[PDB]
Length: 50
Length: 412
Image (cartoon, rainbow over all chains, first blue to last red; front, side, top):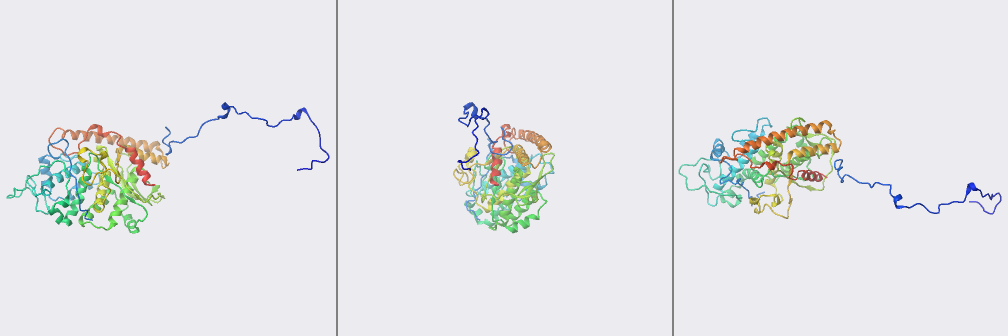
C-alpha cells in the first residue's frame, strides 16, 4: 500500500467506469440445483447397477 | 478325543413302513460284501469321475452313500440294542462287529429290532464302549451317516480357517501333493485316520481343515490364480462340459487378506444334483474326519430341519455356533464364481462365462432328468436305493447367493 496523502492522483469519473460492486446475488431456488446426487451400486462391485 | 456321547443319527424313511432299501438290496449289500468298513465304498468313489455312476442297484455315488447309511441305520439296531438283537439276514460276526453275517445257525434269540427314526448313543452300549479302540474307525463312518441323515438335502459339510498360527511343516508337506485332485488326498486322509485310532495330533487335522477352505474358496470365486491362500487355490480343469475338476494348485499371485482369527461355516446343497458332484461330496467326507477329532458347534439348528430331526439330543439347538446353514444350488454358484472373476477383471465374460454357463445348463438338465427318471422306480416299488425328492426341490433358491457372500466375507 501507498501513502494516500500524495501527488499524481486522478479524479476521473467516467461513464465507462460507473461505480459498481457486488451488492446482491441471485439465489432463486430453481437456480440452486444443478443437479444429480451421487450414488453407488449398493456398495458391492459392478453388478448391482439395478 | 473320546467324545463320550458320540451319539449318531440313523436315517428316516420317506413315508415308508420300512428302512430305505428292500430285502434284495440289503442282501446285495451285506452279503456280496463283508466288512462294515468303507473300503469297498471308497473303491467305487475314487475312480476319478470316469466310470458312470449309474447301475441297477446304485444310480449314483451318492445313492450308494444313502444305502450305506440306511444299511448302517438298520443293522446297528441289532447290536446297539438295549439287550442285543440280531437276526433276519444280519447276526453279527462276533460281538466286536467284525463282519456282516447271515444268521448263525443256532442263534435265534436276538431279535430284529423294529425301530423307527432314532438316534443312538454309541457309548451307552457296554460292548461298544469297551471296544473304544475299534469303535474309532467306525465312528468316522457313523458321522458320515448322521451328517447326511440329519436333513433331506445334499450333505452338511463343515468348514474351518484357523488364521495366523499356521504350521510350517504343513506347508512343506502339502506342496508335495500338488497336481492331484481333492479326491485322492481325501482318500489317504480317511485311510490314515481310520488306520490309527484317532490322534490328538492336530497335524493331520489342521491340514484337512485348510484344504477344505481352499477348495470352498476356490469353488466360490474368492480363491483363484491371482487371489491365493499364499499360493493355494483349486484349479477347475477342463472349461467345456461341466466336469471341471478341482485340482490343488500352487501359484504365487497374491496372498489374500488374512481373516479375523477363526472362520467357520457349514454348507448344504439343496439340489439333488449333488449326487453327481464328487467335489461337493468329497468336502463333506473331509469335514467328517475333522469331527472325530473335534467338538464342532452343536449342529445346525433345527430352523432348517424337518420335524423328525428336531430336538435331537445335544445336536440341534438355537443359540449356539452357526445357527443357520449356508445353502446352495450348484448351478447358480458357478455363475457366482464367474461374476467375481469378472468383477475382478481376471477375465472377459464375453466367451468364457457364456460358454461354461451354457455347459452347466446342459449338465443340470441331464442330471435332473436322470435323477427324476430313476426316482420313479422307488417312487412306485417297495425299494429305495436313492435320495427322496420332489421336482420343486430342484429350484434355483435355497439361499444360494447368501452362502456365497458369507463365504467371501469369511475370507476377509
